[PDB]
Image: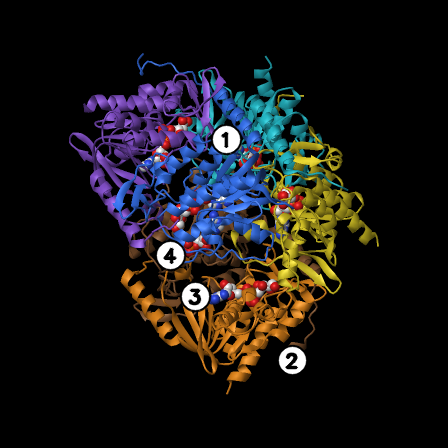
Chain colours: A purple, B blue, C cyan, D yellow, E brown, F orange
Amino acid sequence: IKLNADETKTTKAILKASFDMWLDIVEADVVIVGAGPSGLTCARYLAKEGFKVVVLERHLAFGGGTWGGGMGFPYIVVEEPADELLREVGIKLIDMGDGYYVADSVEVPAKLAVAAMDAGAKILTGIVVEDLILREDGVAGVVINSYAIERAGLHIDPLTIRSKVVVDATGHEASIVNILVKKNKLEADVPGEKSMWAEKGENALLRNTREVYPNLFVCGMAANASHGGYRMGAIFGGMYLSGKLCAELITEKLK
Amino acid sequence: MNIKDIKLNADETKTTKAILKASFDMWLDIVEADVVIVGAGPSGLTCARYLAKEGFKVVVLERHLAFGGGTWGGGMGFPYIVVEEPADELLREVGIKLIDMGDGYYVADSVEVPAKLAVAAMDAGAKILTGIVVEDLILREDGVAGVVINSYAIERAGLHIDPLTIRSKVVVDATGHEASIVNILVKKNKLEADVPGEKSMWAEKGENALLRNTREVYPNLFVCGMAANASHGGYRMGAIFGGMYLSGKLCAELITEKLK
Amino acid sequence: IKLNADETKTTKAILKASFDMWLDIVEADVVIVGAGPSGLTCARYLAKEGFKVVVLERHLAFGGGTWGGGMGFPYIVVEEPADELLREVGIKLIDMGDGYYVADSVEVPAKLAVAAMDAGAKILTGIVVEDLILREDGVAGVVINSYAIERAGLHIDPLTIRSKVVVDATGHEASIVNILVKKNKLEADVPGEKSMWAEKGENALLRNTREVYPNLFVCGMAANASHGGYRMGAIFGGMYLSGKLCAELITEKLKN
Amino acid sequence: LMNIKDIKLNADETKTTKAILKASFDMWLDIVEADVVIVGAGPSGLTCARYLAKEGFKVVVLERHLAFGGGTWGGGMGFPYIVVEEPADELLREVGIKLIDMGDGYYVADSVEVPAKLAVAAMDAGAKILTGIVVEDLILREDGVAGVVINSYAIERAGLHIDPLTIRSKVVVDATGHEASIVNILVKKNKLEADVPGEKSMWAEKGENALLRNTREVYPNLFVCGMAANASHGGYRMGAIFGGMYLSGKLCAELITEKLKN
Amino acid sequence: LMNIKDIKLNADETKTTKAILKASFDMWLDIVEADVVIVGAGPSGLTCARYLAKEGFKVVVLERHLAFGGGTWGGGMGFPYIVVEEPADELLREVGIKLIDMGDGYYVADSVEVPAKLAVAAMDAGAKILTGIVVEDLILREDGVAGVVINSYAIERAGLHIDPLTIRSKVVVDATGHEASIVNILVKKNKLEADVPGEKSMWAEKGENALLRNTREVYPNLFVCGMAANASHGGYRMGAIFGGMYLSGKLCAELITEKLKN
Amino acid sequence: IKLNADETKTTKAILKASFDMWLDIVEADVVIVGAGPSGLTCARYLAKEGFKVVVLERHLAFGGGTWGGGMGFPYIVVEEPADELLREVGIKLIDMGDGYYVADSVEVPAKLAVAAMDAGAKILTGIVVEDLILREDGVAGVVINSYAIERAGLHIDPLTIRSKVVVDATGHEASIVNILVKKNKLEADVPGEKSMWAEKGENALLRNTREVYPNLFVCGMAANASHGGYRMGAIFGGMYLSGKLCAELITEKLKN
Ligand SMILES: Nc1ncnc2c1ncn2[C@@H]1O[C@H](COP(=O)(O)OP(=O)(O)OC[C@@H](O)[C@@H](O)C(=O)CO)[C@@H](O)[C@H]1O
Ligand SMILES: Nc1ncnc2c1ncn2[C@@H]1O[C@H](COP(=O)(O)OP(=O)(O)OC[C@@H](O)[C@@H](O)C(=O)CO)[C@@H](O)[C@H]1O
Ligand SMILES: Nc1ncnc2c1ncn2[C@@H]1O[C@H](COP(=O)(O)OP(=O)(O)OC[C@@H](O)[C@@H](O)C(=O)CO)[C@@H](O)[C@H]1O
Ligand SMILES: Nc1ncnc2c1ncn2[C@@H]1O[C@H](COP(=O)(O)OP(=O)(O)OC[C@@H](O)[C@@H](O)C(=O)CO)[C@@H](O)[C@H]1O
Ligand SMILES: Nc1ncnc2c1ncn2[C@@H]1O[C@H](COP(=O)(O)OP(=O)(O)OC[C@@H](O)[C@@H](O)C(=O)CO)[C@@H](O)[C@H]1O
Ligand SMILES: Nc1ncnc2c1ncn2[C@@H]1O[C@H](COP(=O)(O)OP(=O)(O)OC[C@@H](O)[C@@H](O)C(=O)CO)[C@@H](O)[C@H]1O
């Protein structure tokens, strides 16, 4: 095989493509912060509904804290009936009894990401949300920068993405909600997660998945961190449901 | 039934035991395999796809917690990678959307690619283990007999802890420009041979050498992707991946032949 | 000598045994956090009593802050009558007068660990307790991860060990009691150790060794740190007695 | 016969501090001359130390880390069991270590139990173990190696420029694992024409069996055992199987006993 | 006599090692009880130490770094001179330090000469200086402060979990500079209802004069001098001018002498 | 007491005096690199002889590796007859027998430094020698920078000090001799110190203290490092004698 490869043609193709993408993407319907299990589920459902969705993830790879499974052991758990949310995306499960299923902790994030992308959602990695955009209305988008710039420690201004809604799906950090409260000196505490009580934790998640400030929703562990809910460890049924519920709430508000 | 109105039954011990139990059946099974591929990059995952379709038992080992290698960042952070005719079929094959940029050049979302390559590999039967470092090789008189493994966490943490092993009929170095498995072989076993490393950039010379350079370099040890060019002093090509995909496929064909 | 050694047989033996240990260990009667002198003493006494005991230690080696003795000088001190707690485990002592004895600071942790293990206690090193498990009842176990993962800085979920009781034997850090208070936003301060007053410190230890929250006990310096007690330096009599007392208190609560 | 909570304990800062000083001071003045210095409190070094001390020699084991044990604790990739094969399993049994039979002459042992019990055996046999102590160099005479140059691990980690002290000995043993760090010091600093090749890749059988052949006096008064032996002679490695380590240590003690009773 | 090159020197490892060990132990066993402990071998602490030792007290100065001197060496922003103003210049002259007159009662001195000569004066007056030694805590009695809890700088930097030793004293002096680290320990660990405010911004005149007022016993048996005094009382700072530092140290010695001859 | 202290007057005095020192110091007779025991002894003797001497030291404090004594134990050893080199500077010694004396490891560097400074030598600390100055003649001085700049990792050009002679007294590093050889691609190896043999080591020091390249002398451990000599540990007699000898050799070469 003769392959025709040229530096300039390669460079320009990347540049050209990246530009059409960037100019288009800086206005969107929904921005999801965090490409974890809850954020990617939310993204799936919103995109199926025809919304223009961007998922932003600080690390170069999506996935959040799924890859390592439980203490390095590469399986994660899902309980009935949230297992359907995995089946529905082609993820193979193993039945371990009593409504408990496991899945390869590398297979899960891959297939959740593909579902999201194939549903229409855009995922940008290597991108840090450092702040929010505000209007009198409430939250109006996100202020973004490059992970590389952040790690490198450089003093460089950001860019923006305007959106109708922002979703904090950043895990136990609840880092977008914290930014809102700290920088805008709101009289409210983000308490953070309590200790482990899997049952209390999993069930609180759905109650705690809501709009916490105008145009700002939380899902996944960010929801329990924001409302002082218990944690559940390497069981993900509530994560997936929270993401879906979050998409339903947003769909309602936005139609 | 309403999604707000769901009772979830979640228990710490049941969760912990399920993960332990499943990890064990996996581990006890996986430590003997037909082929071990080192590196979950574009070449290694392509190779894994083809070998698994052929019914071989394949393990891909990757140091980082996420697969993908150096695809995610695309070109200098700009999140698209290039593929040239006819290697674009190797992407289409796997559901990856391409944009035609002219002259047989296509781009693809640099996040979409590694995801879809990984899914293909896994759906073809290949097992991918991340967070796992190959620190050494296993030898027999025959030649290479498998890999010596440890955890990334242990490595980063700097702890002095012994490894485990995976025996295989074949090992593939798909570790990129590092060519780290070939280097280990040469350095530790004091072989009279130099791993020269990649030359400077000449995309055309580089892309075409890749296929010539994708071969068995020592008994039971194959190289593909940039590891092939690094091992043979070939030029590099930058963020164009047609040769990577073809190298991976070729590497699978060579191994299939040897192993049938 | 011809030795028959094989990679796969070696690997599978390790995996098989570990896998068996793990499935069994994630439910236990008592979890002791910290393989220091107090935690290992507690572990000895509870295991003699037939309880199923796991000691968890973040570092790969047990021992806590015994090894370096005093400012690097490799001897630690024990005072009458706590010296019996060392002799009973085979530790050689040197009489320095006035009811003071010293012991080789390397010999001590080794022999405390052996006693615990031989009494039935299991010691897992390289393991960090990052959180607690709760029920309405009170503390229900511990949330664990690997030291390697922690040092490496990786974002990886934990596993669990359920237990009837948890013991904070983590030294002056009192890190388990702190986790409880901080994360569950309890209205209470963990004051931390006061300055050195060896006599006040040694004697307070026994008063301070107790159940501080349902199913959570403290012993060793964690006890004084939790109750704002004085410290005593490289003298360990109270540490050993605290561990023993802590085992007695737990035995009482748990035998039924 | 009382509530433990009531016991009156007499504890005093000065008495505590002086007891530690006094005892360390006696220990140090005595220890700086010895028959054998073993560098590395790993499985091979501690085994060696057991056997030499039983024989009545004055033995010091030096270990850089605060805890003894070497790379035993983490077992295999974190999984806390190590393997031993027939007949080296007796070297564990004899020290009270419980073994589980896994078949085909393979036994496992709790990776935390092993180093503890090896250390206790050594100490109870008479050996002295000093942790937190780095060997940074050797002492020489025309005769050959004459002891070790020592410093504190704390000082080393802290990066401070501080002179060392010494321990004179008739023999030195490099039991420092794959580093073979004492042999390397000898060669590098004294510009000897010889290469320390380092370990080859894994071949457990070739590796385990070479260990016994490779356990020897490599330079006058300097022995190697454990992985240091295979590293020094370009031998293969064997992973988390320790039968050869234990035998190497024992063999090393036999070779030294022979040389020194002469 | 001869060309130096031909001198026969008798040097032996063991004799060297045992001499150091022997002398250190006599020193350590003696030093762990003292009249006064000064924390910080800076300009104020070393001055204080001079005056207390001249008075016949048994004084130990403890310094974390291997070298004494505090923040004198670098002078002002690296420029190696420090300033002293009339009449505190006599406190330098009296110790042999050469001064250059810059006018208006301002003198400079070589920033390397000063710490050296202050240290020599202290040592020659009888004071003992131990470097490489960190004070991590205080010793208490109902009476008040009863000494210091000490550890090795090496151990601290290395990050090791190792217990300390102690030095009992009638008085402790915090001469640790703007950190006021001993006073802070007292307050933080013993949960005293009092704030250590720390130094204010620069106002050299207000700062220099407050120092003498602020040099006092702040808790029973605990004195402050030097910048620790201003840090403890929220006083202004003065920069690279040291007259008040020297006077503070001297005043501190006078206050202590008074208390202790009672 | 009313003290008159002013920021500007303070700042200007420091600046004024420093600039005067700097403009004068950048030409000197002898530059000694390393304020250790050998370098400071050499400096004493050269300055007594009327030469203009600068000692340069990277760390903010002088002293080299004296302060910590032996493995932290704060005493260093000196053997007959080199003990006179310490008594002559006011250092108190303790007789430990057989011609061995010890001295407080903090007292020694202080008093060596004072002697040097009082003899006329200038000591500049916080100053790194990063390179040499050359002429056809041979070595012509040193290229200097600030320790702070080096540690901070900043890319900043240096300044210079011209001298008739340069002395490498940088200890076992022998860092100035190494710079010469590496950067100027001389066909010669700096072997570095051998292992410990105190007697061989101490005696070789005097033979090894010499001019190794035109205008470049070595003393102290740098001498043994340069010539592959054995080391001797915390015994300093040879260090002191090496420094003195080095001053004698330089005096001879330089008096005319
Ligand atoms: N400011 C930010 N900008 C961009 N990405 C961010 C930012 N902050 C966090 N992230 C990224 O957001 C993602 C969060 O994924 P993560 O997986 O932590 O969130 P989740 O979807 O709620 O699931 C939590 C579970 O993994 C597990 O912990 C659990 O069940 C609790 O016991 C991760 O991939 C982060 O790197
Ligand atoms: N010892 C090891 N153990 C496990 N994984 C390893 C080891 N060494 C390397 N890897 C892993 O190997 C993976 C794949 O590497 P990588 O993605 O570099 O290899 P590739 O498939 O040939 O692709 C090369 C292109 O990305 C690009 O560079 C190019 O076109 C040349 O100009 C990366 O994800 C590494 O983390
Ligand atoms: N979160 C955690 N998970 C696991 N291990 C932990 C955790 N936190 C601490 N540890 C481990 O707990 C152990 C504490 O042992 P440590 O020896 O500090 O505790 P102790 O038994 O009360 O004895 C204290 C004395 O050493 C000394 O301080 C004294 O006499 C007072 O002046 C050490 O070995 C830690 O590594
Ligand atoms: N210069 C030094 N001074 C003091 N201790 C030292 C020095 N250099 C190394 N050590 C210490 O020496 C000890 C060596 O113990 P290590 O366990 O490495 O040596 P070993 O006895 O031969 O056993 C090797 C096995 O762990 C395993 O790896 C195997 O079977 C091969 O695949 C460790 O505890 C080091 O910290
Ligand atoms: N816990 C501790 N243990 C031992 N030494 C300590 C401790 N904490 C601090 N030190 C040491 O104490 C010494 C304090 O010396 P320092 O020089 O800081 O104190 P000073 O005597 O008041 O003089 C201050 C002036 O240098 C100057 O800055 C000024 O005029 C204000 O603008 C320094 O050498 C520290 O390293
Ligand atoms: N490039 C440089 N620029 C400036 N200073 C330097 C440079 N390189 C080294 N130094 C400084 O030079 C000084 C060397 O003093 P050092 O004390 O190492 O040298 P010495 O005077 O020969 O005495 C050696 C003994 O301490 C010890 O080694 C021994 O007897 C064991 O065999 C130290 O104070 C360094 O900081």
Instruction: Describe the element under mark 1 as helix, strand or loop.
Output: loop
Q: Which mark is residue B87?
A: none
User: Which label sits in the foreground, 1 or 4?
Assistant: 4
- Quick check: D57 above or below A80? below
The residue marked by circle 1 belongs to what chain?
A: A
x, y percent for residue E145: 49, 41
The amino acid marked with disc number 3 is Ile
Q: Nearer the viewer, mark 3 or mark 2?
A: 3
Work out how far the residue at label 1 is from the one at label 3, CA to CA, in angstroms: 53 Å
Residue D153 vs residue F191, the one in the foreground: F191
Find disc 4 in the rendering and name its residue.
B201
Residue holding disc 3: F127
Residue most extreme to the left:
A136
| Res. A115 visible in picture | yes
Q: Tell me which corner region of the image, top left, top right, bottom left or bottom right, holds residue D189.
A: bottom right
The lab-note entry on whether marks 2 and 4 share a chain reads no
Amino acid at dot 4:
Met
Q: Residues within 10 Å of mark 3 (few under 14, many from 20)?
A: many
Q: Quadrant of the C terminus of chain B?
A: top right
The spot of residue B62 in percent (x, y) is: 47, 40
Q: Return the mark for residue A73.
A: 1
Residue plotted at (39% across, 45% down): B70
Circle 2: residue type: Asn
Residue under circle 2? E3
How crowded is the residue under tag 1: few (<14 C-alpha within 10 Å), some, or many (20+)? many
> Label 2 neighbourhood size at 10 Å, few (<14), some (14-19), many (20+)?
few
Q: Are marks 3 and 4 on the same chain?
A: no
Instruction: Confirm if mark 3 falls within 8 A of ligand 6.
Output: yes
As rendered, which of A154 and F51 lies closer to the eye? A154
Check if mark 2's residue and mark 4's residue have beta carbons within 8 Å. no
